[PDB]
Image (cartoon, rainbow, N blue to C red):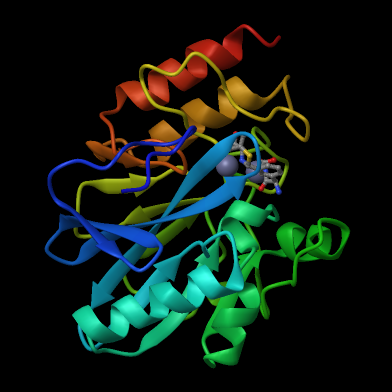
Length: 241
Ligand SMILES: CC1(C)S[C@H]([C@H](NC(=O)[C@H](N)c2ccccc2)C(=O)O)N[C@H]1C(=O)O
Ligand SMILES: [Zn+2]
Ligand SMILES: [Zn+2]
């Protein structure tokens, strides 16, 4: 059993598949978890989502690596056996975009914030093949997110990074904060090296206001939590100003 140094542990309702862990969150939503083995430190878990939308599947975030991301695709093939229409990746760091080449090799259409695509080559990442753009209030421009089904993409403002985006799952009470949101018991906001410490608090609160009726908040490095993940993250971020 993988026991990560950073990230949630395995509990009841988790399926180990190869090097990854999968957890069903709703009838049509699963969390994927992959692990970066840091020598002398141990495993760092990172989470994304898999959403079934009728006869097709949608993915939020890659795993840390191409091979792990190919394992996500293998899990989808075994457990769902429907084609992946597209993936949305939530900023230009390894935990979220490290596996782009596996998605591209599989022929899956990839989407990211235009700014993530512009930053990708500066972050040792491969850009997504399509760029999302956003309104002044953070909502994605719908012409840039064709046929996204239940994925409702929201740019909350700079926080964990300047490019971080978030995703609500319409038809459910789930919203995904990626690395912007930390859980209600977290002591740290994680890596602030690329963060906007001035705007972080407002960006965390904007995510909450964008999906005001989401009761299950999914994030990169903890198990799904209540809305207290949002409010606690914002309270920690208030201390940065
Ligand atoms: C879990 C992290 C502290 S590391 C991860 C990310 N870092 C990477 O993906 C790096 N490539 C990395 C380098 C060394 C060890 C682990 C990750 C970041 O900088 O936001 N997201 C951070 C976070 O979400 O706070
Ligand atoms: Zn990051
Ligand atoms: Zn992260």
